């Protein structure tokens, strides 16, 4: 037992991380087969980032302007291409360490592991959620751009995130591996509004189930509720509205615990309206929304 | 910016994890050079764990009773030995993936990454602290025994923990890699008292520094305190007493922030006596003690 915010083992991704240099700027890239993926702002000076014309800036670069280094190995760049906001550098060598992989565009509220890297070298791994407003609350310093987020499904690494920018607000934004930003953001150093965030209700419910499974039951109450009544409270507290799809996803956890989804909603309602009276749930004094129903089942069944 | 509970990249450790089977019991082992390390209770039935005589139980085993599997590879066991509470199985092949490594006995209050494994396969990685009372609050299911905790220092993996048991209280206990338990625990299924825990004060101070660095400054106050006055409050709140060694370790963080250690102690005092008034610090509604001063500096300087 016990419940931890758990990342995926990072080895498979560690083998794909490289350093990419173009003029003065250095950041991380992802080396899969004979392609290196990295943020296209690797081609920008710090002055350029105020208002870059990426097409013009890239036209001034040739294959040999891109300096790609895997550990001490140098890769030879034989093609370059811009797809949305990623650069794809064709290199002459297939990464011997390419895992089985897919590129996926995750949905807001889903979770993934981030391997934070600097200069193409891994620093740490942590689990995080794509917020409803498509930001992430990460740990990313200068040089972390191009670090990637992923999930693992048996043997297969599903890459879902490439880090591009820190907003002035301190939250993080980035793209899928086809270079499309999550959310309304652009790769330019301007004020950008993320817009209102909300709490991922189905994940909070999943974590309350996790808590019941682990012995934390103090929040179970004698009430129930309706979907529409619960959603009136969700709206007041800036929780995402609960739908039947969410109810369905919680089914297995409802079955394991013998607690009906709508009864758990009633417990949650009481916590929203009354707080936690200084108590804790799985060591948190707040309601945790960074576990999905799948995260909880994985962790509970090994 | 941003501050996350960050594990070390696990690849180097993933390559050393194997499955060890002896009679019916299967758990994880650590394959380094030509030795496999695993918990000695791999030789126990579930009945044996009430009161095992490990010497007698092992005398009934031969090299060929130990079934060691790395992925699909089978290792051949050519020697077996019990050191304290670990078994050391000599195998005929050196692990080609042995990283540079050391075995270390960490001190209470230090942190490490855990690669949680089942059947010799990695499931997840997370960061945790050795509690003052030498337990850990992990996520460990049946089959996770032999999973290991580690730190990485450049190229070198310092293994510090092997998981052995879940206490009835739900906390986790284990050994260093020489097989000596941390704390007063034994590898027997009996009630075992962990004894009073306390909060790792120097780590809470380190995390308040982390918060200042990241913009969370609301808790900075106009007071200061003495070491002895602060320690009178620490004792009341079951915080470890602060010493000058701890003050010294916080020096670099005091320097970066321009906040004297004793002034940060005064902020902490006020939080202990007044709570957090429903506020948060780095997204936590509680005082976090699972970051060491070194953890904070690593994360702040990449």
Image (cartoon, coloured by chain):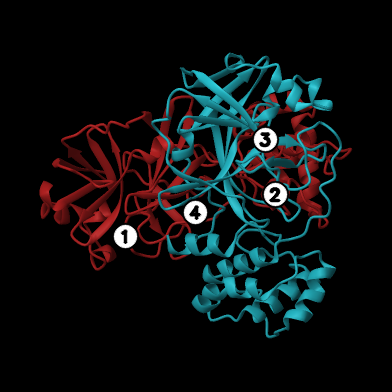
Chain colours: A cyan, B red
Give coordinates of residue A71: x percent, y percent: 47, 22
Choose between A23 and A168: the one closer to the eye: A23
**From the viewer's perspective, is the residue at label 1 or at label 3 nearer?**
3
Query: In the rendered structure, are the residues bearing label 4 and label 2 in contact, judged by CB atoms less than 8 Å apart?
Result: no
**Do marks 3 and 4 share a chain?**
no
Work out which residue is located at the far right of the displayed protein and give it.
B222
* Distance from the alpha carbon under mark 4 to that under mark 2: 18 Å
Q: Dot 1 corresponds to which residue?
A: B188
Give coordinates of residue B220: x percent, y percent: 84, 39
**From the viewer's perspective, is the residue at label 3 or at label 4 nearer?**
3
Q: Chain of mark 4?
A: B
Choose between A229 and B18: the one closer to the eye: A229
Label at residue A140: 3
Which residue corresponds to the image point at 22% horizontal and 33% vertical from the top-left? B34
Q: Chain of mark 2?
A: B
Query: In the rendered structure, are the residues bearing label 2 and label 3 in contact, judged by CB atoms less than 8 Å apart?
Result: no
Q: Dot 2 corresponds to which residue?
A: B287
Question: What secondary structure is found at the residue carrying circle 1?
Answer: loop
Question: What secondary structure is found at the residue carrying circle 2?
Answer: loop
Give coordinates of residue A167: x percent, y percent: 79, 38
Which badge, 1 or 2, comes first in the chain's sequence?
1
Q: Can residue A39 be seen in the rendering of this structure?
A: yes
**From the viewer's perspective, is the residue at label 2 or at label 3 nearer?**
3
Q: Residues within 10 Å of mark 4 (few under 14, many from 20)?
A: many
Query: In the rendered structure, are the residues bearing label 3 and label 4 in contact, judged by CB atoms less than 8 Å apart?
Result: no
Q: Can residue B85 be seen in the rendering of this structure?
A: no
């Amino acid at each position: 037992s016990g419940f931890r915010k758990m990342a995926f083992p990072s080895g498979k991704v560690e083998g794909c991380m490289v350093q990419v240099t173009c003029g003065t700027t250095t950041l991380n890239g992802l080396w899969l087969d004979d392609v290196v993926y990295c943020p296209r702002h690797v081609i920008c000076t710090s002055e350029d980032m105020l208002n870059p014309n990426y097409e013009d800036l890239l036209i001034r670069k040739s294959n040999h302007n891109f300096l790609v280094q895997a550990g001490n190995v140098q890769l030879r760049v034989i093609g370059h291409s811009m797809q949305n906001c990623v650069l794809k550098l064709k290199v002459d060598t297939a990464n011997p360490k390419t895992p089985k992989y897919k590129f996926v565009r995750i949905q807001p509220g889903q979770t993934f592991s981030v391997l934070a890297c600097y200069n193409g070298s891994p620093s740490g791994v942590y689990q995080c959620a794509m917020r409803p407003n498509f930001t992430i609350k990460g740990s990313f310093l200068n040089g972390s751009c191009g670090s990637v987020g992923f999930n693992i499904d048996y043997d297969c690494v599903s890459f879902c995130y490439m880090h591009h920018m820190e907003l002035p607000t301190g939250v993080h934004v980035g793209t899928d591996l086809e270079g499309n930003f999550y959310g309304p953001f652009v790769d330019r150093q301007t004020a950008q509004a993320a817009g209102t965030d909300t709490t991922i209700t189905v994940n909070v419910l999943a974590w309350l189930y996790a808590a019941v499974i682990n012995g934390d039951r103090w929040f179970l109450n004698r009430f129930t509720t309706t979907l529409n009544d619960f959603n009136l409270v969700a709206m007041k507290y800036n929780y995402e509205p609960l739908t039947q799809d969410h109810v369905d996803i919680l089914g297995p956890l409802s079955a394991q615990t013998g607690i009906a989804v709508l009864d758990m909603c009633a417990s949650l309602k009481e916590l929203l309206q009354n707080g936690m009276n200084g108590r804790t749930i799985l060591g948190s004094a707040l309601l945790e929304d960074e576990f999905t129903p799948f995260d909880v089942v994985r962790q509970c069944s090994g």
